[PDB]
Image (cartoon, coloured by chain):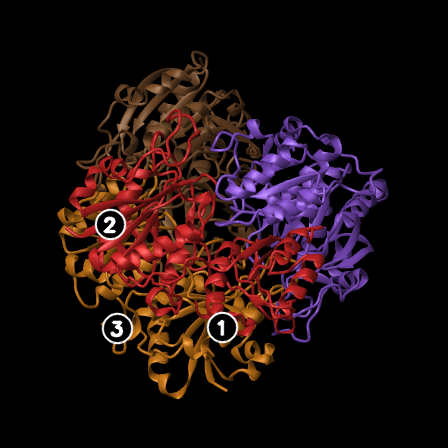
Chain colours: A red, B purple, C brown, D orange
């Protein structure tokens, strides 16, 4: 059977709580072996090898776990047939996107999580992990970029996002849809992201021990500009705006950001709106402010890309081209 | 025909562009009489009295337009049979939630906007105004709280949210659905919000010239606690966190807010996630920290209720009671 | 603890497959006791009594089980504090509606299924059933009509429909939304169906042993009139048309029906389209044809309402009014 | 500018109604010339040549218009740069899919319709047509198969379906997402159907004057088997089943289909469930019966593929492999 490596980072899939009929739980109560031994069917589909990379709740995911993860996938790619990275649901969409642009290993790279902790009744973790391996083991998964497999669905790392705070069906690719659906151990892939991923990108965190500082500001009515200023005073390399509607900023936040952009800070306009592209050629003249419109990339994902882009360039027109290709 | 007061605030609906086939536009280029003079069919269903309250794009909505609108409607309630607020789409969902709680008139109060400026080919403002007037003039709409009428659909101001950055069908009550749908100038109503609104709320802004300071901090991987710390230094009365997953906070952010709470800063846990409730009984001990769980209230809606909750109390336990009633 | 009656009809929830990782299966493999006894946590929230009414797959569901369930729930309303009906997922939305119009018991009546067989990994039935009891046991679930509890969501029996062929989250009230969400054994209800249900309807099946014959014919390009002709030829009482777009019929189908209507057959124009209403005032002159527009009711739900109206009247306009209130 | 040929078939796009605020209307009240002239900006992006193929409501679409339509794009492929087919929205997803399997012209073939009649307020027709021409004129649209452009979204003819009976944003590719989004005249493609279309299909209707006889039967509780027998007695070559749940059939329907299959009749199992695949390896042993699982092809789309499969083979297995490829 395929040799599949399971890089365990923690999350709800490893979390347990008081009971099955109680929602309480804490992340990372089990290790990579227990997860695997708990799903002995894995043994009929892949020759599994587990490794605990970290054991955090993804709310605490950070650049170091990211660098570490990419370096690890790239370094052991040549050694295994595919990967499964067990992770919490909270920031999984951010990590999947980050690996999607820094992982040069085009062998199946699947991320999997669980909305219910391992202790719950009808826990989703087992079958999720089982299905995740079904995907990391399918040859047709190679070259699709880094994937997220949840709820019998194979989702591309760039478009996948967490849609609902508790639903087991929460992961969906909200703008462009899923790449495929799994049924009875089989996947019918009918799509692949056209954006450039993995080996077709220039991002190389192999020698990177740290990613550039990129923060996120929220826009809403009567939005304060303290947050944006706080990030600017601390010298952030970039700031992404979780803007209102089609990428718009509260006037005072727009002020701080325009000052920022004109004095060096990379500034990306994204939106707090869940679906749709933050387009240019709407109300904002990005060209005039040196702002970059983020496309279908939501705030946290636009931060992933800006950080990597900032590793190569500081120019708004350059970053924009990157946001237009990746 | 019934008397409907149209309180104009600006927005795309009252905005234009140099082209009908180009996406660029500037808001607030149109006057209420012009918006109203453009939809002469209005005269066949209502005796319309337009008054331009302000002219801004809703990205610039602030507490004063809220105070103004709240009071204006409250004062003029007996002088008219309903209201229609022409508002930008960016923050229409926050303004509707604020009016929903501060307005004491149970006559149909309907908000309306446009995703396409007045100039665009197939501009949606026209029929949206017709339909919003159809709604404010339907006696069945009374007592349903502040409504948002968009795309032939009547939505409650609490649950209604902008779902897509550009789609005309963007406004959706993502958790509980719409109250009704408009076909041929008639509305089939099959739902009404159960959370207490309008006359049933304890919020009286009639004497208020200002609302408490409530900022929103965003959560993502490697999140900077700078924004949160800036909000606490500025003396913010409350901080709504747009957390990850089910209201979870990044380590540093959590720490800053957990401390802010210990010193009286009301802290609400919301979610960057689009649908679902940031529940209590998951991974955060709201009780140990003095945090309130926002429920289905997204960051920006949670901020509306917090400011108002903050007009009534500072006690997290009571604020939490507020977040469960309204 | 509430005394809850579990009337089991069979379906996937009490079905089984040879494997936890194979999608294959057969319905009606488990009895009610085995079923109930497999979620021993049930006895901690309720005093469950189970009764097998039938043990079929809902694909073969039919008039007699509907009448049997209806009589049984009505006869027994007095002995218990609420009901849970385990049912297959295929036609659960039809029975839910049927019982929503014929059950005069206003104590909680909850339907439940499982998309995965009891034998599968991360099988959904157990928590589904647990949550179905948490609902039938909530006093707040009373007077909401018949409900369907699936995926942590309470959905009114009228609007709820099977949205996906295999997704555990398939069940959704597509037009108006869920009534409430279940988190940690508690339900935050924010809605209730506005149409007349249960004790507010004039349908009494208590003395009925059969229900008027109502068939559904599908419309599509190059639609055959043969199926509609067969229904008319067999002397059907009502024919629901699953039309194209806004209730439209293909010419030879529109023909058989305009005539059938002319000769005393009730004809409801519904739609193959999954959401939205088949309205009056589009392209078809219901008046001229004596056609009843189904409203937001999908073909099969329209069948449920037409059979029951057909027990009261044969008059197109009386029927249309029934379609406008139930 | 590109030479785009507009072939008209009628539909709401060319339908007028007595009022711009009355939902009432009739299709086929405008001609291609008028349609084209109505949106004169078309002239700024293409050299439009209108050709009125037919003038009907798509609820009346048939094999003949489909054969003619395929034959016309095929023959005139060399004389133009792209094709935009105006069409009624009712059976649009059907024609879109017919042409997707029979058209060998890989130059942009784009279908467009409108939900609001031309005479209406905020008519969608104008900009839909404009955007459809943008699409047909973008060389990026070549090779994606036949497209459907509605509500600023480029959708593939295979997965596209009418989701709401009245919403202008009703067209969605429910299972795999849209190919791209149009903003300010530019399309951001991020996907293309992986299933085989146009020239990669062995379907050729160039010499065909009639398609095989395939009808659809509906399944619901107590489903009559009359409609299925009607089609059988009439010698239908194929029977698509709009089944309950995962392609399941009401007992008596099952029997008629099973027996008809045994006598050569091709029986394809689809589902009335709007999204998801009708799979094999569930409750029905397709092989044992000579039935074909339709996959994600809804009943009407599966009727398209079956008629075509039926022009090549009559063998269940060959027909099944066709359903796994096209």
How packed mark 2 is, by other alpha carbons closer than 10 Å (few <14, some 14-19, many 20 or more), is: many
* Image mark 3: chain: D
Q: Position of residue D32 (x, y in %)?
A: 52, 78
**Front residue of this view, candidates A103 and C186:** A103
Same chain assignment for discs 2 and 3: no
The residue beneath circle 3 is: D200
How packed mark 1 is, by other alpha carbons closer than 10 Å (few <14, some 14-19, many 20 or more), is: few
Q: Earlier in the sequence, mark 2 or mark 1?
A: 2
* Image mark 2: chain: A
**Front residue of this view, candidates A311 and D88:** A311
Mark identifier at residue C5 = none
Secondary structure beneath label 3: helix
* Image mark 1: chain: A
Secondary structure beneath label 2: strand
The residue beneath circle 1 is: A321
How packed mark 3 is, by other alpha carbons closer than 10 Å (few <14, some 14-19, many 20 or more), is: some
The answer to whether one can see residue A38 in this image is: yes
Marks 3 and 1, how far apart at CA:
34 Å
Marks 2 and 3, how far apart at CA:
38 Å
Q: Nearer the viewer, mark 2 or mark 1?
A: 2
Marks 2 and 1, how far apart at CA:
35 Å
Q: Position of residue B134 (x, y in %)?
A: 70, 50
In the image, residue C7 sits, relative to residue D320, either above or below, namely above
**Front residue of this view, candidates C312 and D265:** D265
The residue beneath circle 2 is: A5
């Amino acid at each position: 059977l395929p040799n599949i490596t399971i890089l365990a980072t923690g999350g709800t899939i490893a979390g347990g709580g008081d009971s099955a009929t109680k929602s309480n739980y804490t992340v990372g109560k089990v290790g990579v072996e227990n997860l695997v031994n708990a799903v002995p069917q894995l043994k009929d589909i892949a020759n599994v090898k587990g490794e605990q990379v970290v054991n955090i709740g993804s709310q605490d995911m950070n650049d170091n776990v990211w660098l570490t993860l990419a370096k690890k996938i790239n370094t052991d790619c040549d050694k295994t047939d595919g990967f499964v990275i067990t992770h919490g649901v909270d920031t999984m969409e951010e990590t999947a996107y980050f690996l999607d642009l820094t992982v040069k290993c085009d062998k199946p790279v699947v991320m999997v999580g669980a909305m219910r902790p391992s202790t719950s009744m009808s826990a989703d973790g087992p079958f999720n992990l089982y299905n995740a391996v079904v995907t990391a083991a399918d040859k047709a998964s190679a070259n699709r970029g880094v994937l997220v497999v949840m709820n019998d669905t194979v989702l591309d790392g760039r478009d996948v996002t967490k849609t609902n705070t508790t639903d087991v069906a929460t992961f969906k690719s909200v703008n462009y849809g899923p790449l495929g659906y799994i049924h009875n151990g089989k996947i019918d892939y009918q799509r692949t992201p056209a954006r450039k991923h993995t080996s077709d990108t220039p991002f190389d965190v192999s020698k990177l021990n740290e990613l550039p500082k990129v923060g996120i500001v929220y826009n809403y009515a009567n939005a304060s500009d303290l947050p944006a200023k706080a990030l600017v005073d601390a010298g952030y390399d970039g700031i992404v705006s979780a803007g209102v509607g089609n990428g718009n900023l509260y006037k005072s936040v727009f002020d701080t950001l325009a000052t920022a952009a004109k004095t060096g800070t990379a500034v990306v306009r994204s939106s707090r709106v869940p679906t749709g592209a933050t387009t240019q050629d709407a109300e904002v003249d990005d060209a005039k402010y040196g702002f970059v419109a983020s496309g279908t990339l939501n705030p946290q994902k636009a931060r992933v890309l800006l950080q990597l882009a900032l590793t190569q360039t500081k120019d708004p027109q350059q970053i924009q081209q990157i946001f237009n290709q990746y």
